[PDB]
Figure 1 (cartoon, helix red, strand yellow):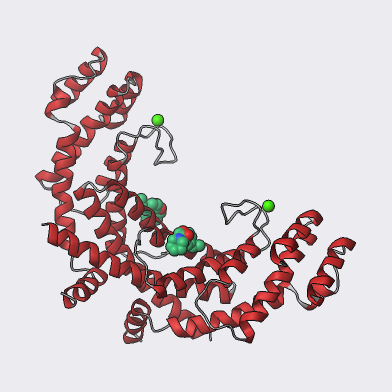
Figure 2 (figure 1 turned 90 degrees about the vertical axis):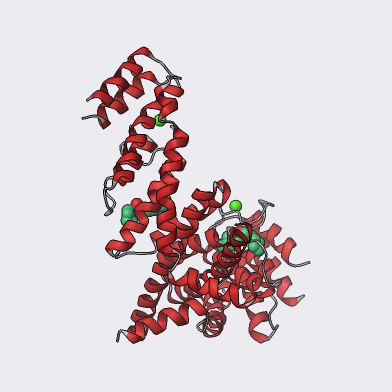
Length: 204
Length: 204
Ligand SMILES: CCc1ccc(OCC(=O)N2CCCCC2)cc1
Ligand SMILES: CCc1ccc(OCC(=O)N2CCCCC2)cc1
Ligand SMILES: [Ca+2]
Ligand SMILES: [Ca+2]
């Protein structure tokens, strides 16, 4: 009776792990495709499954970090969203913290995404007329030539500066989608998706 | 590209169906065991997965009805919970509506559970001092000898009447748990649980 209960709990943990990988893959695909409503609904399912998991492997923590990173990027222009206990941290600042914590290679693409999130974290404040908040985000992030241009734009209150058009929100999204394509290729072979794909193929 | 997107969506529907059955089995087990917090967390996961499913088979609708029925029974004493668009309907009345909609045999146990939910739907109002609400629940449900005793208890404001101790909330819960055991036996062979169980067994 107690051994049965324990074996059932172990099986529920195995199934939750399979469900987390599948939901991460669905979330990545919705982000890549721009399917806003599917992303919202999948994020809700991923959060609920995560609250039912206790012990995590290094791989499951990385998968969770990727889900959290994409959620903050999707909410990057929503300055009323509070993702951290410190209410001053903006969504792109929260995405930057996660980006620097994921156990992943620090290749050229990693650094390009990092710097585009930093510029846009300031740009989104400027675009909403939040000039003092842009200065505070700048101080938290920066924590020389790149830093100096940003402080100049902030002090001029140059909301639609040409610098923000060369390192735009769309360019940040496109670089992030390139990274998402690599996660989709790596997780396409996860148990639930493979089994579901085999079922669909066998009926064709 | 469009055929690939369509095949991916079909696989996501297959996986969501497997996830719904697994979450129903986990929800049933938490209800049977009295694991209140696991029931709450599993209900959250089941609701989110359900919102990501569009077309349902007759079997999936029955599985969803069972999840909804157990949620209303678990909230039976929570008279501030509103499960229907009509705010007057109490949680046990909402459970009674679902019980009469499930495609299932109407054996002796089905009717015993039905009548215990009817008595308790009135009993829970009386126990909270809501005498006028008990009369209104009575009129919505009833909709001869059984009906007459209840109307007499309601009019006397006999909160802790002996009739409610013979057909108690605990007796209703125990009869419902007997039914839950049959659902657990029928869904223990679902894809995700079987595969998870095989993994756990292979490591023993
Ligand atoms: C957006 C997806 C999401 C993910 C997790 C979460 O809460 C849990 C949480 O933060 N951790 C921290 C990381 C390890 C798991 C527990 C809420 C929402
Ligand atoms: C408690 C579990 C739960 C289940 C379903 C749900 O909403 C969806 C809903 O009602 N239907 C009606 C029945 C068919 C699916 C759509 C909310 C919570
Ligand atoms: Ca804010
Ligand atoms: Ca009420």
